[PDB]
Image (cartoon, rainbow over the protein chains, first blue to last red):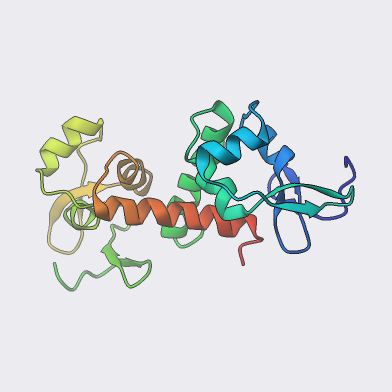
Length: 98
Length: 98
């Protein structure tokens, strides 16, 4: 699971992805500064239990909308980077995308 | 000031803009659901007093970064649309911009 066969390559960040575009939830947890269990996160935030085969058989999965809704539910340092990124994209889309 | 000579055309929304890319702060207030004075907003949120000629002589101005930092400082309905938009752009930039 360290040589994922599909990745969403966003910055220097490289998240593993299912053929239908769900993210590898472990990796999501690293990028959002969670240390709680994925079962705990799912319960706390009203997220669906989903799994996808990321090349290592089924593992927990999170949709991109939901990864985002979490980044803005958390207050970790890491989730704040994600949030700041969301704000910068809004700024750039308003300057003409440039 | 209803036929602004430069507009940032974002959605159906059309904000007036200075030659150096500042937004018309009145219009910013409408779009962010403020009814307080622009002097009050400037004080409350730690914004600079700026003015630009938007075709009607100098009027208060707000930078795009600052319009954004406010949309995420407010909790109005309108500022929430702006925020939701910031989240959608993050989602799309992660799906490849598509």
